[PDB]
Image (tube, rainbow, N blue to C red):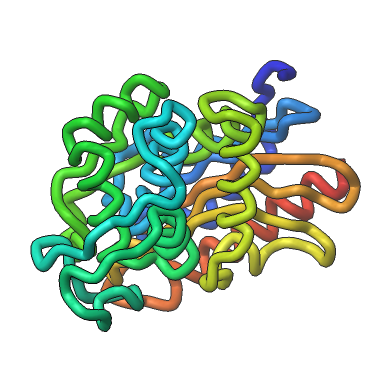
Length: 264
């Protein structure tokens, strides 16, 4: 990869947009794989992860598959202690009913299924075991403190953690080629695309995972531009409950960066 080269001008403009919003606290990190152009505006700060942490969890899932510790077809049980409200469809099924591991992992991501997420976290050895794995990958502030949906926001991450994990995955680290491609497919098929994707130009594609606990909103992933360029992106915003300004801010920053890389 090319060296990191701050886009000083654009960084400055984003910090201005951010800082002139009273009751929002934003953090973001973008990195262009071709040019090395980078953007870091509160990117290292710790945020409640909300559902963005499901991305690291998915990586851990496919790591276990690669290592033969989990199989794609093994049956996982929706135990009463794992059932969780908020996003998801498994919660409406019979307690102790069973699902193929890959189906559960996919639902965790595509619809942010919180029951599926608890099922996967439990199958992979629990929170502590995953927290250890996240540290191994260089995620410094990505920690699972409680089950999902974790509406209180106890589980943490950072924009830099999320984007750098995606950088590694994009570049073929951590996961096998088969698992990598499965992961990217799943992360192209999520149902919440009102944040980073809404700032992208026609023909761009994005593998990503959103998170929203009302009090925090964020998104992270990898964008492929029609011009051939690739970049990773992550942004988190602390907001008043369901404040549309927080989600619009992500859209605005997504658009600014997309258009900057278009012109460059």
